[PDB]
Image: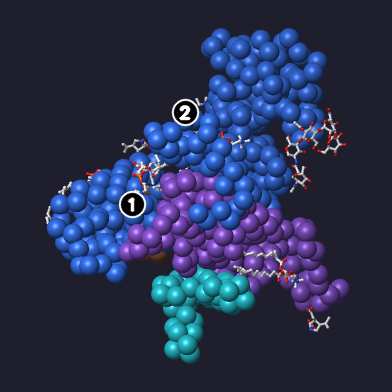
Chain colours: A brown, B blue, C purple, D cyan
Amino acid sequence: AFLTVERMESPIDSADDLAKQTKIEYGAVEDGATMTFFKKSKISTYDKMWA
Amino acid sequence: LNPLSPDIWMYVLLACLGVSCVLFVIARFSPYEWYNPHPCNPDSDVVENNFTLLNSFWFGVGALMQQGSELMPKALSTRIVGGIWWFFTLIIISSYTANLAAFLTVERMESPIDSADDLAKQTKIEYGAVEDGATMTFFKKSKISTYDKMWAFMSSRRQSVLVKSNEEGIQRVLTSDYAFLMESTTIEFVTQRNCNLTQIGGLIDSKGYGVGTPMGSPYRDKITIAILQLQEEGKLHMMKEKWWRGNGCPEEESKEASALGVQNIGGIFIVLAAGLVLSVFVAVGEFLYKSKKNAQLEKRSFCSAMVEELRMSLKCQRR
Amino acid sequence: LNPLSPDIWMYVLLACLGVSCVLFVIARFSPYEWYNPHPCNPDSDVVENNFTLLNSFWFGVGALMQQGSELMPKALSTRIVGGIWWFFTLIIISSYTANLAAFLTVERMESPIDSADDLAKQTKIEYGAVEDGATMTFFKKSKISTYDKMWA
Amino acid sequence: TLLNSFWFGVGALMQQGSELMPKALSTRIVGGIWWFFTLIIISSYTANLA
Ligand SMILES: CCCCCCCC/C=C/CCCCCCCC(=O)O[C@@H](COC(=O)CCCCCCCCCCCCCCC)COP(=O)([O-])OCC[N+](C)(C)C
Ligand SMILES: CCCCCCCC/C=C/CCCCCCCC(=O)O[C@@H](COC(=O)CCCCCCCCCCCCCCC)COP(=O)([O-])OCC[N+](C)(C)C
Ligand SMILES: CCCCCCCC/C=C/CCCCCCCC(=O)O[C@@H](COC(=O)CCCCCCCCCCCCCCC)COP(=O)([O-])OCC[N+](C)(C)C
Ligand SMILES: CCCCCCCC/C=C/CCCCCCCC(=O)O[C@@H](COC(=O)CCCCCCCCCCCCCCC)COP(=O)([O-])OCC[N+](C)(C)C
Ligand SMILES: CCCCCCCC/C=C\CCCCCCCC(=O)O[C@@H](COC(=O)CCCCCCCCCCCCCCC)COP(=O)([O-])OCC[N+](C)(C)C
Ligand SMILES: *[C@@H]1O[C@H](CO)[C@@H](O[C@@H]2O[C@H](CO)[C@@H](O[C@@H]3O[C@H](CO)[C@@H](O)[C@H](O[C@@H]4O[C@H](CO)[C@@H](O)[C@H](O)[C@@H]4O)[C@@H]3O)[C@H](O)[C@H]2NC(C)=O)[C@H](O)[C@H]1NC(C)=O
Ligand SMILES: O=S1(=O)NCN(C2CC2)c2ccc(F)cc21
Ligand SMILES: C=C(C)[C@H]1CN[C@H](C(=O)O)[C@H]1CC(=O)O
Ligand SMILES: C=C(C)[C@H]1CN[C@H](C(=O)O)[C@H]1CC(=O)O
Ligand SMILES: *[C@@H]1O[C@H](CO)[C@@H](O)[C@H](O)[C@H]1NC(C)=O
């Protein structure tokens, strides 16, 4: 069991993994096209990411 | 032979030559190992050690395969050598047989080609694209080294390797030995629903689709903004998800199976049969060297050999 | 009996009767195996070989099942048969007990579908409903694009 | 004896062999088929113990 575990897996592997886990905080740049993507999205995974 | 790295298989083979050396050294000048022979003795003047160099290396090989040898050390200085070699061979085997669960599965080949570099240097796999597309025309106008070699090939054989549709290409990958050079998006569909086809390589260039308008038409700019409108809403991702996803060919895991055969294990019977043929040769070596030791008392080579040969034929000689 | 295929169980038994006869021939052909079975008795030139054919099988059977036998090779020509049969049966036992772990812990039998989108992709198992019920009327008005394919 | 016959059954069960091995082929088949028993019982034990 100790020889076959895994390297170290990140607690997130996607965007909805970081949408649920509110321990690691989001980021973007002020007035870029990244925050402008979430400001106009309504896909309800990315809506929480702007919430 | 993989669950230990090829320096570990050398370091445990030097450890057998190392410990059987230091067991042979200690057993000679430890004065408590020199025991008494003759179990019906007039109480002595004879001391005989049972650690030769032949028996010290039989202890290192004996205590390595967990089948113990005929001799165990006396004389505590030679028991600590035997006591710490046993903890060595315990950990080497318990690390071997606990890692062997993963390395005991065969795995698929890599393809003979793995890019457009590997596929330009070969002649066995024929290759071509759809004639008069944007893929043939890319190699027709290219000048870079690899992608001009791949058009020197196609222009020599433009009746045989250049199919005239994608469906004539996908069937010829199937029904022949052939590598067909598509666009990246059609391969993302075909390799889903079909499960014998894969995308060998990375993207050669990068180019995109587009609603074509006549040169001067104002519907250029009104669809330019409109295509951007579906993208940030996520409709272009939603429509592509609906069609390019199908039966995923999920058969990669597929544990479910694999009784070991002569494919997996397969090779101990080679190193068994190479060990016995080795042992027949050193049975000749003992047959001659003892007869040449008997030739230190009498005739040259033949008379001492044939007497030992004839007693072996009776199978029950017992002088 | 499963973690080795039924040919390998017939190559072990043909090696266990193979090596145990090669050990018997070499042990009576080697002159170093013949010893005087009287250490404390200087009586005469009596020689004795421990390797009869029934003791030679017992080394190949005793070392195949990890238990070890009463006799042990003494000449170098028979320590190489005995030394390589130990390495044979070290790896056969280690390959058996490492694949026997895999056959005891697989799963019962899993269905190829576990959801609706699993049966939306897999078009091998065919759909069903009742004509003019509220089941087909649910898919006829849905547009959720998982259930839209299920009416497609 | 009966003390030594049961020490062979307990000896050959924990894989540490006993001081006596049988002669007389009829008593070697008993020892030869008890060894295959205790091989499969332990190799099923230590492969399920994970
Ligand atoms: C089941 C088999 C039984 C075997 C037998 C019983 C075995 C008894 C064994 C007991 C070990 C006790 C130590 C606790 C182990 C926990 C970890 C530890 O502390 O290791 C530490 C060192 O410790 C050593 O190096 C120990 C060396 C053990 C040698 C035993 C030889 C006896 C052989 C018999 C002699 C024959 C004499 C014969 C006489 C006639 C290192 O710790 P670490 O991991 O590096 O942590 C740091 C991690 N970090 C680097 C990330 C910061
Ligand atoms: C294809 C190749 C074929 C070769 C064919 C030609 C080979 C020809 C053969 C040559 C040698 C055999 C005949 C001469 C020696 C006689 C044997 C003997 O026991 O005597 C001496 C050897 O004692 C030693 O020194 C043993 C050498 C080290 C043992 C480990 C060797 C490597 C194991 C192999 C793995 C490596 C793998 C290698 C790569 C694969 C000492 O014993 P003694 O003192 O005489 O005892 C008398 C007993 N008495 C006193 C009670 C009377
Ligand atoms: C413990 C210390 C001893 C160490 C010795 C051993 C170290 C040796 C390490 C060698 C490492 C070499 C590395 C590379 C080799 C490449 C060759 C190769 O391809 O594989 C070759 C196999 O190889 C054999 O068959 C060797 C068998 C060894 C038998 C000797 C046992 C000695 C027992 C000692 C008893 C001690 C008792 C004590 C005595 C007192 C050929 O394979 P192939 O080409 O695939 O042919 C198959 C045909 N086919 C192609 C159709 C499938
Ligand atoms: C690694 C350890 C090596 C051990 C040693 C070598 C072991 C050699 C073993 C060889 C077995 C060869 C059979 C092939 C196995 C494949 C399956 C099979 O056929 O089994 C079949 C029966 O078969 C038996 O019952 C075999 C009984 C084996 C007894 C061996 C004792 C030897 C001990 C030594 C003697 C001491 C003498 C001492 C003298 C001094 C049943 O098949 P099934 O699964 O029921 O399929 C039906 C499935 N269905 C019901 C779903 C429809
Ligand atoms: C001597 C008599 C004759 C023997 C003959 C036969 C013996 C043949 C023996 C060996 C043969 C083959 C040798 C190869 C492996 C050995 C060394 C090695 O590399 O291991 C380690 C050395 O890495 C270290 O941590 C160094 C620590 C040294 C401690 C003292 C060593 C001496 C012990 C005496 C203490 C006396 C106290 C007790 C006194 C009672 C690991 O190497 P690494 O690559 O660095 O690790 C990976 C690095 N990583 C962690 C970043 C991932
Ligand atoms: C494992 O991989 C092998 C290596 O590619 C592969 O072998 C090839 O198999 C195909 C057929 O599947 C062989 O095609 C033949 O070539 C002629 C043209 O010269 C074909 O017309 C012909 O029949 C075709 O095969 C179709 C099946 O794919 C069949 O429905 C049609 O009738 C069609 O006409 C021949 O069959 C090709 O030469 C083989 N290559 C080599 C190097 O042997 C194996 O099929 C593959 N096995 C599996 C199970 O996937
Ligand atoms: O043909 S394009 O319009 N211009 C070139 N490129 C980028 C250079 C890769 C791309 C990249 C992605 C496209 F979808 C289109 C184009
Ligand atoms: C550095 C900045 C603010 C720019 C750079 N490219 C993006 C842009 O120009 O839209 C921004 C990065 C982002 O969106 O995180
Ligand atoms: C038997 C039938 C057709 C009826 C029964 N209840 C549902 C109904 O009355 O709506 C239907 C079942 C279904 O939807 O599969
Ligand atoms: C892949 O292998 C052969 C070649 O076509 C065929 O028998 C098999 O059914 C194929 N599998 C699929 C999923 O097409």
* Residue C79 visible: no
Residue B8, percent across and down?
Answer: 35, 45
Q: CA distance from mark 2 to mark 1?
A: 31 Å
Residue to which mark 2 is pinned: B300
Q: Residues within 10 Å of mark 2 (few under 14, many from 20)?
A: few
User: Is B317 left or right of B196, judged from the image as shown?
Assistant: left
Of badges 2 and 1, the one in the foreground is 2
Q: Chain of mark 1?
A: B
Where residue B25 appears, x then y in whole percent? 20, 48
Classify mark 1 as within 8 Å of ligand 3 or not, answering yes or no: yes
Query: Relative to the observer, which residue lies in front, B78 or B39?
Result: B39
User: Which residue lies at the image location 70% right of the left edge and 46% below the top edge?
Assistant: B195
Q: Amino acid at mark 2?
A: Arg
CB-based contact (under 8 Å), mark 2 and mark 1: no
Identify which residue, B81 or D18, lies in the foreground: D18
For residue D33, side relative to residue A45 (left or right): right
The quadrant of the picture occupied by the N terminus of chain C is bottom right
Judge left or right: residue B31 versus residue B155. left
Confirm whether residue C34 shows in the render. Answer: yes
Of B207 and C118, nearer the camera is C118
Q: Are marks 2 and 1 on the same chain?
A: yes
Tag 1: amino acid: Asn
Q: Which residue is mark 1?
A: B55
Question: Where C102 sits versus D4, above or below?
Answer: above
